Image (cartoon, coloured by chain):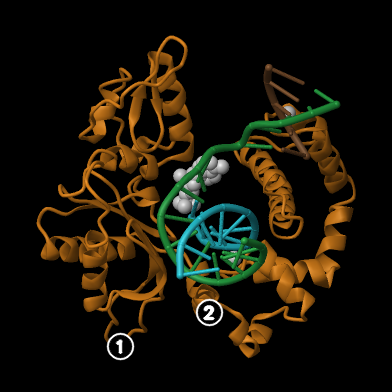
Chain colours: A orange, B green, C cyan, D brown
Amino acid sequence: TLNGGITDMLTELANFEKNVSQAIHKYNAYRKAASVIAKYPHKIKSGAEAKKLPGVGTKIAEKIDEFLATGKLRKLEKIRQDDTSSSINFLTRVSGIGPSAARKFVDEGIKTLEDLRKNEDKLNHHQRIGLKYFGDFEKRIPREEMLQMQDIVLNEVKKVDSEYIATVCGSFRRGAESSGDMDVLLTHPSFTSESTKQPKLLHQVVEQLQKVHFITDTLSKGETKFMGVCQLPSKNDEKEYPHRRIDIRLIPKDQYYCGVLYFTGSDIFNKNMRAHALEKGFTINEYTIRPLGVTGVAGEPLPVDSEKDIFDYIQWKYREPKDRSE
DNA sequence: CCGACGTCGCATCAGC
DNA sequence: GCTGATGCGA
DNA sequence: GTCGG
Ligand SMILES: Nc1ncnc2c1ncn2[C@H]1C[C@H](O)[C@@H](COP(=O)(O)O)O1
Ligand code: NA
Ligand code: NA
């Protein structure tokens, strides 16, 4: 209502720049421009007013002038009508098809899901699974579902080994009523840096979840990370729950809790905590915490074993995930 | 002017 | 066959 | 595209 019309404009140009022009840097720029505006409690009456905000320059200021004066963006309308560009942006929506594949497909005449089904012998394992759950992937995951899903993973991860620590991070940790992705992090005492690579640990857990029919498909799998699809048990009378995305990541006990807080969020929280860490003399790198020197030479990573453990370094108190928004 | 805007493990591909 | 670049996803 | 050395 306020600046929703402008934000929608910037977000469209953002996706265009990512999928069509393949300019991730201009994509992030347009995305950042829409962010600061979405936090502005006032109706932007002119581009000059918007340029004041960090992330908005002259180009975006001029665009707003046209959007308010004419009622839309002239350059944006040409993009929408352009069959070639509008189709490329669509194909990328499919998990597996990126900005490169989408273009290669359109050149061959493949532009829709219907056209994809015909030429399925041209899609790899990932691209096929994506097409299969095209809609199920674009749907949001309610907290209640996340809770039910969590119990299963926790029950199965402990049922296979009591020394397994698994915590679902992300928006879920912050108490979000939604999620859209099930990011799980796990560790074991038998895995601590110096310890040799463990292709048995992650594989062990994955097999157990597939054993109870939770994990349906697999996008990619290795010795440390896992990416696939999952689904809750079919309910009586009612229709079965949609297929959801799930990522499992094995992390050492030395980088576990340090890696937990990072994936716990938020995106703004990481920035504020990264800057404050440097103010005291420490530097965060997702994995460990290093005490830099007078010239900035990071030293030997100091021991970490908990969530508050890291706060007991930068003179900060334990801030609850429900408040780690900013 | 003009270069920096995170990352990185896994699957597919190129070249040798 | 092995090595190394490129594409993809959060 | 937007910022800052
Ligand atoms: N450019 C860049 N650098 C570093 N981290 C980034 C960047 N862009 C996004 N993110 C992080 C911020 C969130 O923790 C996560 C997305 O959360 P999700 O719930 O998966 O949408 O990705
Ligand atoms: Na600005
Ligand atoms: Na895609």
Which residue is most to the top?
Answer: A294
- Give the class, few, some or many, for how many residues have Cα within 10 Å of label 2's Cα (few <14, many ≥20): many
Name the mark nearer the viewer: 2 or 1: 2
Horizontal and vertical percent for residue A263?
A: 38, 45
Residue A294 horizontal side relative to residue A149, left or right: right
Residue nearest the observer in this picture, A109 or A182? A109
Helix, strand or loop at mark 2:
helix
Residue A295 vs A126, above or below: the answer is above
Q: Quadrant of residue A59?
A: top right
Cα distance, mark 2 to mark 1? 30 Å
Horizontal and vertical percent for residue A281?
A: 38, 15
Q: Quadrant of residue A111?
A: bottom right
Task: Give the residue at x 33% y 33%.
Answer: A288
Residue B12 horizontal side relative to residue A61, left or right: left
Horizontal and vertical percent for residue A106?
A: 75, 75
Which chain is mark 2 on?
A
Residue nearest the observer in this picture, A28 or A234? A28
In contact (CB < 8 Å): disc 2 and disc 1? no
Task: Give the residue at x 67% y 35%.
Answer: A42
Amino acid, disc 1: Asp
The residue carrying mark 2 is A128
One can see residue A19 in this view: yes
Which chain is mark 1 on?
A
The residue carrying mark 1 is A237
Residue A19 horizontal side relative to residue B9, left or right: right
Task: Give the residue at x 37% y 84%.
Answer: A239
Residue nearest the observer in this picture, A61 or A304? A304
Q: Quadrant of the C terminus of chain A?
A: top left
Helix, strand or loop at mark 1:
loop
Residue A148 vs A303, above or below: the answer is below
